[PDB]
Amino acid sequence: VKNKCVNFNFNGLTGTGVLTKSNKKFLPFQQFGRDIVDTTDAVRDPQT
Amino acid sequence: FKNIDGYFKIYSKHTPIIGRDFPQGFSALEPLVDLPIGINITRFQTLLA
Ligand SMILES: *[C@@H]1O[C@H](CO)[C@@H](O)[C@H](O)[C@H]1NC(C)=O
Image (tube, rainbow over all chains, first blue to last red; front, top):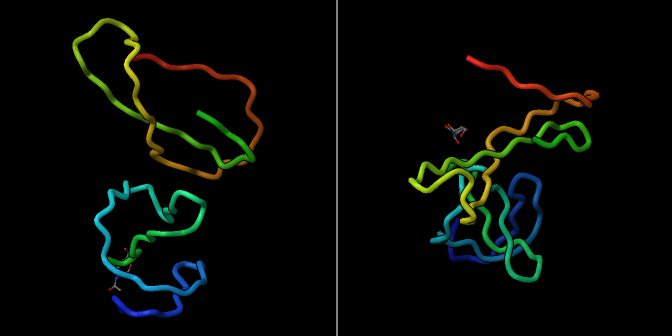
């Protein structure tokens, strides 16, 4: 679900936040992603 | 080619250009295949066509 505060378990990455479609440039090998100070910020959907 | 903790790692990038051999221009290397070999490697050699 998008645009709602939920608890996610993305491929073993457990956490809480709001997920929305991103406009980044994830290369095909890229999996997790992050932000400036070392926190998971943008995770690509493994299915879609 | 790197083989840290087994887990053979390779990276690749292709740049045709028109400059001479080995230009100074920068270029990144994207990973292509990461296969967990996990054996002992010391020697290295190539092949031809
Ligand atoms: C199953 O995973 C494969 C791998 O990408 C892909 O077809 C899709 O994400 C999934 N298919 C489904 C859920 O029908």
